[PDB]
Length: 295
Image (cartoon, rainbow, N blue to C red):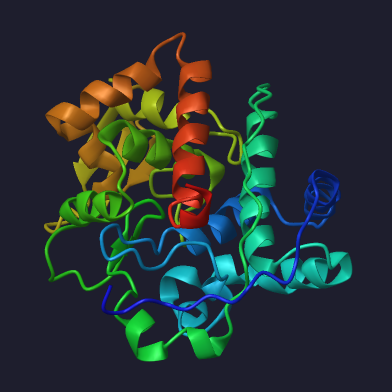
């Protein structure tokens, strides 16, 4: 109430066939699944329930300061291309198109998992100007951790796994939603980083449930590499090969009572369809967190 971030009147109004031409422009753009999903996730995940600031509306991912955040350094590499596309289409905002990109990325992911879901998209976002994006006040929002992206700074404040809860609650996520969300993001190759931490799959960019299966496989022994236990390795008990690395955000999903009961739904033989759905559902939740006009 006391601080609101201004947004401009929409200068665009895409029809359902604009959108579809846009999805096909993004699809033919050269951006990988992981680049698509990263740029969208990085737009949307600034949301803070209650305060209601941040979110994907306004494309402030493209503005200062978010554009310089360490968390975003890889996500932001996608913007030149998406910008070029928004400008040549002229049917929709950078904001709407950063999100649509995530949408193309998830569906493309899911159709490699030999799935075929449609990711609900909601048009209408506008682009904020730098002048409606107060630097000092979005500075407060730079995240200390985003376990959805396996990002973690300032190792002396609180803990990696507690910051995961905090983050998820900020986005108003339920436990299954965080869960679905984390396991999806891992397999789509959306760490903030190049890290392979938690990327438990041979096929990155396939929206599989590998994260959950591999997470709970007794074939794998997990051990901290050093006294901080910020980094683990999953060694294959058979071959003795180090197959996987993991952070605390990855592994808390197998240590915690509640998170674990959820990961086994999703590691279940028959669960793929259930997880993909739940991912898409939680995915669209985050994308739309700030879409007040719509509700």
